[PDB]
Image (cartoon, coloured by chain):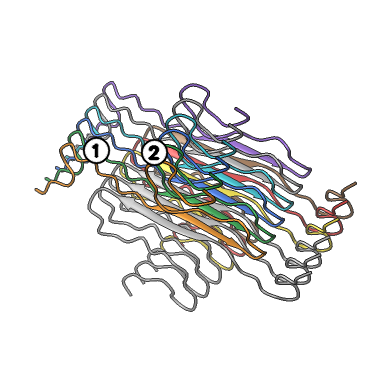
Chain colours: B purple, C cyan, D blue, E green, F orange, G brown, H red, I yellow
Amino acid sequence: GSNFGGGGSYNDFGNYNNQSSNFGPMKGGNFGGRSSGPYGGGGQY
Amino acid sequence: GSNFGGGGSYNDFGNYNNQSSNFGPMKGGNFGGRSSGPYGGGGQY
Amino acid sequence: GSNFGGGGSYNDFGNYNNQSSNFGPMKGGNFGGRSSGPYGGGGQY
Amino acid sequence: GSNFGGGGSYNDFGNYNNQSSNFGPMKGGNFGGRSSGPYGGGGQY
Amino acid sequence: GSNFGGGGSYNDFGNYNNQSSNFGPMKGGNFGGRSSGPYGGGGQY
Amino acid sequence: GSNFGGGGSYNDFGNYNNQSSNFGPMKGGNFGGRSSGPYGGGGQY
Amino acid sequence: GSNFGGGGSYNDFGNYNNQSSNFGPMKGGNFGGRSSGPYGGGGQY
Amino acid sequence: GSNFGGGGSYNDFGNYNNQSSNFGPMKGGNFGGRSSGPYGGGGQY
Amino acid sequence: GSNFGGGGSYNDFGNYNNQSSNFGPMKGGNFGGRSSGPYGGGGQY
Amino acid sequence: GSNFGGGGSYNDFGNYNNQSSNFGPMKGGNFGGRSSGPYGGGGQY
Amino acid sequence: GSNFGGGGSYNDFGNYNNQSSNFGPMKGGNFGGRSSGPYGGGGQY
Amino acid sequence: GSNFGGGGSYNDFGNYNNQSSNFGPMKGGNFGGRSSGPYGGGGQY
């Protein structure tokens, strides 16, 4: 009889995938991975 | 008799996929991965 | 009878993936990995 | 009967992956790894 | 009956990976590893 | 019945990896390892 | 004027997705990922 | 004028995803990842 | 005018993902990662 | 005019990911990482 | 005009990741890392 | 005009990661690191 997240627990556990593959010349970018707060994620500015 | 997220638990567990593949020259970007807050995700500005 | 995150515990445990592979010349960038706070993530500025 | 993060514990334990591989000449960068606070992550400025 | 992070404990224990491999000439950089505070991470300025 | 980080303990214990390997001539840099405070991490300036 | 896979090149570059999510008790398995050769893929025998 | 896989090159570059998430007790397995040769992939025998 | 895998080169460069996350008790296994040769991958026998 | 894997070169450079995270008691195993030869990968026998 | 793996060179350079994180009691094992030859990888026998 | 692995050179240079983190009591083991030859890797027998 074990509690597993019961109560008001905010239980966020999701798998996330960003995948990209290119044979030719890649000047651009695939910006992946979690981010939070204003302007999260990478790039120019 | 085990509780599994019972109660008011906000139980968010979803698989998310962003996948992209290109043979030619890739100047642009596939912006993947979770984000939150204003202007989340990468790119110019 | 063991509690596992029960109560108000904010239990965030998600797998995140950013993956990228390119045969040609790569001038651009795949910006991956967790970030938080203003302007999180790498790049010009 | 062992407590495992029960209470208000903010229990953040997620696997994060940034992976990148390129055969040609790589002038750009894959910016990975956790960051927090203003302008976290590496790059020009 | 052992407490394991119970209470208000901020229990942050996540695996983080930044990996990169290139056959050709690498002039650029993969900036990995934890950082905090303003402008964390390496690069020009 | 042993306390393990219980209370308000800020228990931060995460594995972090920065790995990079290149066959050709490497003029650039992989900047890894923990940093904190303004402008943490190495590079020009 | 750049060749991009021209000639007899067998150019196989397809995105493939296997995704599955279940709230209840999962005794079975979602067998995903590429396989080749006799009896490829996992399971009993 | 750069060749990009031209000729008889067998150019296989595809993104593959296996993702799975379950709230309840998981006795079974999601067998992912590339395999080749007889009986590739994990499981009993 | 640079050759990029041209000729008979077997150029295999694909991103592969195996990801899995479970809140309840996990007795089973997610068997990921490349394998080759007879009976590749882990498990009982 | 630089050769990049041209000729008969077997150029295998793929990113591979095995990731898994579980809140409850984990008796089983996620068997990841490359393997080759008979019965590659870990587990009982 | 520099050769980069040209000829019959078997050029294997791939990033591989095995990552796993668990809040509860872990009796089992995540068996990661390259292996070759009969019965490569760790575990009972 | 510098040769970089050209000829029949078996050029194996891959990053490999095995990472694992657990808050509760860990009786089991994460067996990482390269191995070769019969029964490579650690564990009982």
Residue closest to the eye, F5 or B42: B42
Relative to D24, residue D1 above or below:
above
Asked if marks 2 and 1 touch (Cβ < 8 Å), the reply is: no
Q: CA distance from mark 2 to mark 1?
A: 33 Å
Residue at point 44%, 33% (across, down): D38
Quadrant, the C terminus of chain D:
top right
If the image is split into quadrants, where does the N terminus of chain D sit?
A: top left
Q: Residue furthest left?
A: F1
**Residue G29 in sight here:** no
Task: Give percent across and percent down for residue I45.
Answer: 43, 66
F20 or E16, which is in the foreground?
F20
Which residue carries the number 1 mark?
A: C4
x%, y% of residue F45?
A: 51, 48
Residue identified by numbered label 2: E37
* Between marks 2 and 1 in the image, the one whose residue lies nearer the viewer: 2
Crowding at dot 1, Cα within 10 Å, few <14 / some 14-19 / many 20+, comes out as many
Question: Can you give x and y, in whole percent of width and height, for residue I35 in the image?
Answer: 56, 62
Q: Is residue D11 left or right of residue I4?
A: left
